[PDB]
């Protein structure tokens, strides 16, 4: 809510991805904190298992509700940190409601 | 059956009443057969304690003779040493504060009588630094003795050489531990060592060493004088001899009396000392050996008596024989809770099980006094307790677990109610 | 001659007098879970995570410490020596700060594994945790020492392998913190080895702070060229750029240690 | 400090090009036998695999830690 | 006295 | 346990054993075995404390210097023991025993009285720097449970107003009869001396043969 | 309730020694 | 803990000896896994004979072949481990 | 440019992809957002940091706000706490 991105680059979302989709490289941000310089989910590689949703300790990477993201070009499907963070900002209100409804179950 | 005679009683100068200084000591006749004893032989001295069957007068109980026998093995070119720990951090051990302050000499000749038994080159006495005044008394006494030539090279007009020194403690209960007294003497942090290199084998400064409770060193000259048998008779079987008993808390006249061992617990508050404050039925529990030993509740107590064999049958330890008594007017849950607070403020932290475990029980115990914790947590602390009991490098973790075990063992219903009390008011 | 016979769960190995119980298990092939015991560092007995059960004995013994005696069969997988590890791991973890996704000794932790193999499925420490104050030990080692399991291998290495004799324990109780009393940097060659030798990720490398995570690192074994001792080293490369160089053991040349320059 | 990954012999093919990818910056490799590391229980068996498959081999002898004498009593020696 | 034990110590030392 | 250099507590505060102190220092050294300077640091650290209660970082460095030991070695010893104070100590520095034996016999009782009399929280020095109160643990002498060691005053068996009386004595004048201020001598059954009320047997009494 | 372009966000990894612009 | 039924472990072990005796040739290391599963191991030459006995023996009819697979242990001289699972 | 600063120089090829197109960059750059966060004052020596919401936060860590000299920063939220 403050505005600091949740991911702290533990990189086990990369470890458990079955398809090798997520690529993460990180370095200490000047703040001294730990953040990901590059976070790239290759959606064409991703098979939408939802384990990344499962694995994240801070729950920074989530399976968002939108299913309509069909794209004219293959490159658009590859997603870097800025698209995903932008995707996160757009759907945060519903993502928060969805996680709110299902967290007791998990 | 106790009721030892005054004549038989070891420290006649107890309670002062006689000059603690040498001239008082000479009227005591403490230095009477010292030359003869040393002359007899080291082997003669250990024969006397083996016949006495004296048990360790400190918290741990072991045959005193066998412990001294261990470093009686031939010297390997390193000077053998004597260490007397006058530290008594355990609550209720004002037992030792007496001999040191009231009868310093008895311990001085205890040191040389003991010294030739182990062939120690010299003895260092670690009186707790807290007792600064106490120290003032002993080295005045030690100074007298050398001036006399009782101690020093050719001590007591004999071939044997001994030098006695006093070392300043610095407010640590753990300093008391046998391997840790040494390290404080060595000048490193007071952290116990593991037993595999035993104290005799690796000594202070790598020179064979032995450690004795001051009471243990003090009685050795008188036991040699009175003979092991005289001393042997008073005791019970393995248990033997008179050991000073300190009764403190909820008793009409708290005092340290050197009455005989094997005393019915009901008898020593009722007959000597002061009957339990408020009546013998106002006894929620008795701590026989001090904080380290588990407390025993009233129904068990009079039945049992104060000797180490009887207590181990009872699941408690004679220890320093410090009797702490708790009337029905005390929150035991809080009483034992401060003893765990006594151990978190004091354990060295060298070993993982004591460091976190004792702090963990302290946190749970504080919640237990409030009653915030649920009833299921109470046996949880049981299990945390035995994890600490067998895994610790020294015995203090042994000691921290026992009071916790005693509270759960006999006062489990009361703790559940404190559990219940808080749940009801929400 | 000089070959006491000792039993490792029965294998009945024969060992030189004076070998520790932990060492006896090693020649059979068993591994005692251990912290605070490093082969080229003095035995300290701080953790006691290595408690084993010699047969017919009342208490369990400290593996790294007890010299094995004649005909004492070690029972390394008994019902007791597992409660002696299931209950120690309870304690190390109790005061531990769970920032494993911060601790860059994530997969390089000798404390999650031993928890994950020899420790307990769940925690009972419903009480609160402790915290220490991060200080500066220099520009190479990042000491997030709230992680420290007070295993005293640093204080040893910093005194025994390197002659710095600076790092030391300060205080008693559960706030014994193993950091320099006054803030004096640990400046010496051989300095970076502390990272490799602290099994916890309390103090780790500051340059390689958060650039990687060990499962990814592809490890190629090569030779030190910065100095003429030719110390053996392992270059850990991820996706084609070197991420860290850490020592690999060569008995004769660098026995598990490398210089501050060549890492 | 665990030694369970220093037990079985492994034979690993020589490392090859890992150029950066222009579009996403991901590492890219043209060598198929790169990620392949076969595990063989004994030195003799691994050498056999290289000979029949025709790959060149350069075996490195196992180096195991030398026995080291340790005793808690020894360091307590003020002498040394 | 603050130093009486210590003064007694070198009295012991001679 | 971290010494963040402060103008007051830092080596700018020069420390050196008084010619008289240095003398004492060696007396300690020869008491200990030959070639073992290290054993003398706890006693030498104690005399630095005797010199000055504060014992700042400068003082510990001197101790290590005089005793030629790794400085840390001294720092570790000072931190481990409560006897040493690494912060300024009140002139009187009273310490109240609050282990279960004393608490059972009312130790806590005393505390409340002393806090009010010193008019200060427990654990810090009075503004006057006159007294410092701390809740110390078992100080021995339990038979006499109510207890408050003030620089070895070890007053024992003290009723609340007693201490107030003692504190006043300390506040105006000095040496307030340190010791158990109740009729009993040293430790003695308040009733009397059941242990030995007879005269002590003299030298060579019933000395066994052999 | 009441076109993107993908790119590497990480920077260069090996810096080229730049030739001295001072002629010699 | 899985619900092991020792009743099985024994009966299948007993069959394992039965087969081992019936075909002393071609059959070695017959063992019943801790999973209540038997795994007769046969010399490669016994492929035809051991199967046929199991397909056509009144006391051991093993009519259908569930699977034929080959693990590859590169270390093992004989690389492949053809495994035939029968019901 | 972006959070990290990924940028293409004039001579830099690999910048054509944006020709007649747009790049994905972020307003609300996080680097400055926590810096914009007030310092959580506390009474206790040590404090927790669930991240806010327990299960919906970060693995709880206890921060030692023991030195006013430094406001403890939970390694997960970047929230500075003022003793
Ligand atoms: C934490 C701890 C504190 C101890 N404190 C003392 C003490 O103050 N005095 C003492 O005589 N023994 C103390 N002991 C017992 C010693 O370890 C040792 O067994 C005893 O001093 C030996 O003397 P003895 O053999 O003459 O009884 C302590 C033990 C432990 C574990
Ligand atoms: S996404 Fe969740 S898991 Fe993957 S790195 Fe960022 S935080 Fe760790
Ligand atoms: S138990 Fe472990 S920690 Fe407690 S004192 Fe003995 S050694 Fe130090
Ligand atoms: S050390 Fe770092 S990694 Fe190992 S457990 Fe503690 S936190 Fe998780
Ligand atoms: S720092 Fe690493 S090594 Fe030094 S004690 Fe803490 S854990 Fe053991
Ligand atoms: S490993 Fe057993 S003592 Fe540390
Ligand atoms: S507890 Fe107060 S002196 Fe024993
Ligand atoms: Zn946080």
Image: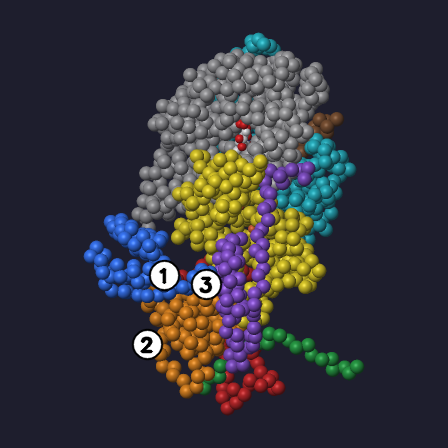
Disc 3 element: loop
Image colour for chain D is purple
Q: Residues within 10 Å of mark 2 (few under 14, many from 20)?
A: few
Image colour for chain E is brown
Residue at the location (48% across, 71% down)? Answer: A5
In this orientation, does residue F140 appear?
no
Q: Quadrant of residue B11?
A: top right
Image colour for chain C is yellow
Indicate the position of residue F125 as horizontal and vertical percent values. Answer: 59, 44
* Mark nearer the viewer, 2 or 3: 3
Question: Looking at the image, which is closer to me, H10 or B236?
Answer: H10
Q: Are marks 1 and 2 on the same chain?
A: no
* Mark nearer the viewer, 1 or 2: 1
Q: Estimate the spatial distance between the alpha carbons at disc 2 and disc 3, rounded to whole Å.
A: 61 Å
Question: Looking at the image, which is closer to me, B229 or H26?
Answer: H26
The answer to whether residue C91 is above or below residue A95 is above
Q: Which mark is residue H74?
A: 3
Question: Looking at the image, which is closer to me, C149 or B242?
Answer: C149
Indicate the position of residue B376 as horizontal and vertical percent values. Answer: 34, 46
Q: Chain of mark 3?
A: H
Q: Which residue is mark 2?
A: G1
Ligand 1's quadrant? top right
Q: Could you say which chain is coloured blue in the image?
A: H
The answer to whether residue D78 is above or below residue B94 is below
Indicate the position of residue B236 as horizontal and vertical percent values. Answer: 44, 18
Image colour for chain I is red
Q: Could you say which chain is coloured cyan in the image?
A: F
Indicate the position of residue C81 as horizontal and vertical percent values. Answer: 44, 43
Q: Which mark is residue B424?
A: none
Residue at the location (50% across, 57% down)? Answer: D42
Q: Could you say which chain is coloured green in the image?
A: G
């Amino acid at each position: 809510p403050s505005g600091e991105e949740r991911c702290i680059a533990c990189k086990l979302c990369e470890a458990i991805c079955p398809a090798q989709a997520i690529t993460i490289e990180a370095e200490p941000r000047a703040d001294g904190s730990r953040r990901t310089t590059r976070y790239d989910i290759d959606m064409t590689k991703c098979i939408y298992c939802g384990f990344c949703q499962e694995a994240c300790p801070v729950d920074a990477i989530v399976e968002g509700p939108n299913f309509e993201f069909s794209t004219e070009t293959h490159e658009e499907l590859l997603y870097n940190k800025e698209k995903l963070l932008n995707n996160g900002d757009k759907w945060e209100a519903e993502i928060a409601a969805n996680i709110q409804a299902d967290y007791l179950y998990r | 059956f106790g009721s030892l005679k005054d004549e038989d009683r070891i420290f006649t100068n107890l309670y002062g009443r006689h000059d603690w200084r040498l001239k008082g000591a000479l009227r005591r006749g403490d230095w009477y057969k010292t030359k003869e004893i040393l002359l007899k032989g080291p082997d003669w001295i250990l024969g006397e304690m083996k016949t006495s069957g004296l048990r360790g007068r400190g918290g741990a109980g072991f045959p005193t003779g066998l412990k001294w026998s261990f470093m009686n093995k031939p010297s390997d070119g390193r000077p053998k040493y004597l260490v007397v720990n006058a530290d008594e951090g355990e609550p209720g051990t004002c037992k030792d504060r007496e001999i040191m302050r009231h009868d310093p000499h008895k311990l001085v000749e205890g040191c040389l009588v003991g010294g030739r038994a182990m062939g120690a080159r010299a003895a260092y006495i670690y009186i707790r630094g807290e007792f600064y005044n106490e120290a003032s008394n002993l080295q005045v006494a030690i100074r007298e003795a050398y001036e006399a030539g009782l101690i020093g090279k050719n001590a007591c007009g004999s071939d044997y050489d001994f030098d006695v020194f006093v070392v300043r403690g610095a407010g640590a209960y753990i300093c008391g531990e046998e391997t840790a007294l040494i390290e404080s003497i060595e000048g490193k942090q007071g952290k116990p060592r593991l037993k595999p290199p035993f104290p005799a084998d690796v000594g202070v400064f790598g020179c064979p060493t032995t450690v004795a409770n001051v009471e243990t060193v003090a009685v050795s000259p008188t036991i040699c004088r009175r003979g092991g048998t005289w001393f042997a008779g008073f005791g019970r079987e393995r248990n033997s001899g008179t050991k000073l008993f300190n009764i403190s808390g909820h008793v009409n006249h708290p005092c340290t009396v050197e009455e005989e061992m094997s005393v019915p617990l009901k008898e020593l508050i009722e007959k000597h000392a002061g009957g339990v404050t408020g009546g013998w039925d106002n006894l929620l529990a008795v701590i026989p050996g001090g904080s380290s030993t588990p407390l025993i509740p009233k129904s068990v107590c009079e039945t049992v008596l104060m000797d180490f064999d009887a207590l181990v049958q009872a699941q408690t330890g004679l220890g320093t024989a410090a009797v702490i008594v708790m009337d029905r007017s005390t929150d035991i849950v809080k009483a034992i809770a401060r003893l765990i607070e006594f151990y978190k403020h004091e354990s060295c932290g060298q070993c993982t099980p004591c460091r976190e475990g004792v702090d963990w029980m302290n946190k749970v115990m504080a919640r237990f006094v409030k009653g915030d914790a649920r009833p299921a947590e109470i046996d949880s602390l049981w299990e945390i307790s035995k994890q600490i009991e067998g895994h610790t490098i020294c015995a203090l973790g042994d000691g921290a677990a026992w009071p916790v075990q005693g509270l759960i063992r006999h006062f489990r219903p009361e703790l559940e109610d404190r559990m219940q009390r808080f749940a009801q008011q929400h | 001659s000089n070959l006491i016979e000792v039993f490792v769960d029965g294998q009945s190995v024969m060992v030189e007098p004076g070998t520790t119980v932990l060492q006896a298990c090693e020649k059979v092939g068993m591994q005692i879970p251990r912290f605070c015991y490093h082969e080229r560092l003095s035995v300290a007995g701080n953790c006691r995570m290595c408690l084993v059960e010699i047969e017919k004995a009342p208490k369990v013994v400290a593996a790294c410490a007890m010299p094995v005696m004649k005909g004492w069969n070690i029972l390394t997988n008994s019902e007791k020596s597992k409660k002696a590890r299931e209950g120690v791991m309870e304690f190390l973890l109790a005061n531990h700060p769970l920032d494993c996704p911060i601790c860059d000794q994530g997969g390089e932790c000798d404390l999650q594994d031993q928890s994950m193999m020899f420790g307990s499925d769940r925690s009972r420490f419903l009480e609160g945790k402790r915290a220490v104050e991060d200080k500066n030990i220099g520009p190479l080692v990042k000491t997030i020492m709230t992680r420290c399991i007070q295993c005293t291998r640093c204080i040893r290495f910093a005194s025994e392998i390197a002659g710095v004799d600076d790092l030391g324990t300060t205080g008693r109780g559960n706030d014994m913190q193993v950091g320099t009393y006054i803030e004096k940097m640990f400046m010496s060659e051989l300095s970076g080895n502390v990272i490799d030798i602290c099994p916890v990720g309390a103090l780790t490398s500051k340059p390689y702070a958060f650039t990687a995570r060990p499962w990814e690192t592809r490890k190629t074994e090569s030779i030190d060229v910065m100095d003429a001792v030719g110390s053996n080293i392992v270059v850990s490369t991820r996706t084609g750029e070197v991420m860290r160089i850490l020592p690999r053991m060569h008995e004769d040349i660098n026995e598990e240690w490398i210089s501050d320059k060549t890492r | 400090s665990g030694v369970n990954n220093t037990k079985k012999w492994k034979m690993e093919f020589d490392t090859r090009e890992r150029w950066e990818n222009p579009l996403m910056g991901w590492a890219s490799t043209a060598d198929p036998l790169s990620n392949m590391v076969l595990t063989f229980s004994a030195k003799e068996d691994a050498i056999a695999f290289a000979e029949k498959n025709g790959w060149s081999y350069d075996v490195e002898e196992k180096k195991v830690p030398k026995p080291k004498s340790k005793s808690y009593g020894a360091n307590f020696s003020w002498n040394k | 006295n603050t130093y009486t034990f210590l003064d007694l110590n070198l009295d012991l030392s001679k | 346990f971290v010494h963040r250099d402060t103008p007051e507590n830092n080596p700018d505060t020069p420390f050196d054993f008084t010619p008289e102190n240095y003398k004492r220092i060696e007396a300690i050294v020869k008491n200990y075995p030959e070639g073992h300077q290290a054993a003398a640091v706890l006693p030498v650290l104690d005399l630095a404390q005797r010199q000055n209660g504060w014992l700042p970082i400068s003082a510990m460095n001197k101790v290590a210097e005089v005793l030629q030991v790794p400085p840390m070695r001294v720092y570790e010893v000072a931190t481990f023991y409560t006897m040493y104070n690494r912060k300024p100590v009140g002139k009187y520095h009273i310490q109240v025993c609050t282990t279960t034996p004393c608490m059972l016999r009312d130790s806590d009782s005393i505390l409340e009285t002393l806090q009010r009399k010193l008019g200060i929280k427990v654990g810090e020095t009075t503004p006057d720097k006159l007294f410092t109160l701390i809740e110390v643990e078992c100080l021995g002498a339990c038979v006499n449970a109510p207890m408050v060691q003030i620089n070895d005053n070890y007053y024992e068996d003290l009723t609340p107003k007693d201490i107030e009386e003692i504190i006043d004595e300390l506040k105006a004048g000095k040496v307030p009869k340190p010791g158990p201020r109740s009729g009993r001598f040293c430790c003695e059954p308040a009733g009397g001396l059941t242990s030995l009320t007879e005269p002590p047997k003299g030298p060579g009494f019933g000395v066994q043969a052999g | 309730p009441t076109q993107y372009v993908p790119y590497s966000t990480t920077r260069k990894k090996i810096h080229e020694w730049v030739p001295p612009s001072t002629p010699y | 803990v899985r619900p092991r039924s020792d009743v099985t472990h024994k009966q299948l072990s007993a069959f394992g000896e039965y087969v081992a005796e019936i075909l002393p040739k071609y059959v070695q290391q017959v063992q019943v896994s801790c999973l209540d599963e038997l795994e007769i191991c046969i010399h490669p030459d016994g492929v035809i004979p051991t199967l046929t006995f199991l397909r056509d023996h009144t006391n051991a009819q093993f009519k259908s072949l569930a699977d034929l697979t080959a693990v590859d242990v590169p270390t093992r001289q004989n690389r492949f481990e053809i495994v035939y699972n029968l019901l | 440019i972006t959070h990290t600063g990924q940028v293409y120089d004039e001579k830099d090829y690999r910048r054509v992809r944006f020709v007649d197109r747009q790049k994905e960059v972020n307003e609300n750059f996080a680097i400055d957002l926590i810096a914009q966060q007030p310092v959580n004052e506390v009474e206790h020596r040590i404090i927790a940091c669930d991240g806010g919401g327990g299960a919906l936060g970060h693995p709880k860590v206890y921060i030692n706000l023991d030195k006013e000299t430094k406001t403890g920063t939970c390694g997960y939220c970047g929230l500075q706490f003022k003793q």
